[PDB]
Length: 35
Image (tube, rainbow, N blue to C red; front, side):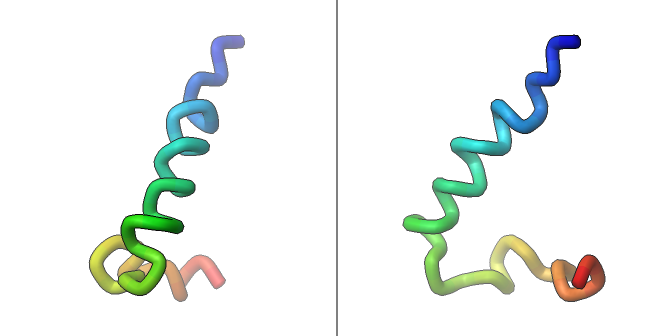
C-alpha cells in the first residue's frame, strides 16, 4: 500500500505548529467535535 496520506499530513500539521502556533480557529475549527 502507498499510504501517502500521513506522509503528506506529517509536514502539514507540523507547519501549523509554527505558522499557526496560536490560531486554531483559523484551521482546526470543529476540532473539539473529535475530542
